[PDB]
Length: 14
Image (cartoon, rainbow, N blue to C red; front, side, top):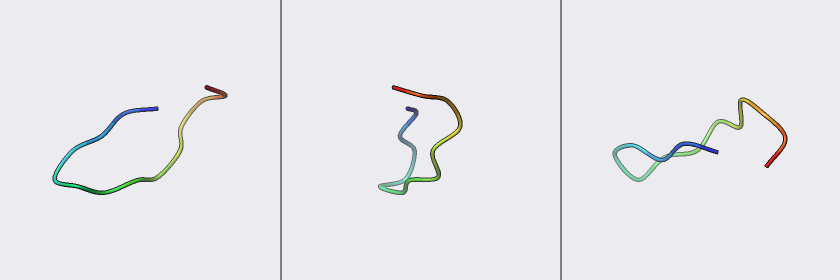
């Protein structure tokens, strides 16, 4: 997934 400002969220299926 994407990483910004040391935070997660999960958008797709890595």
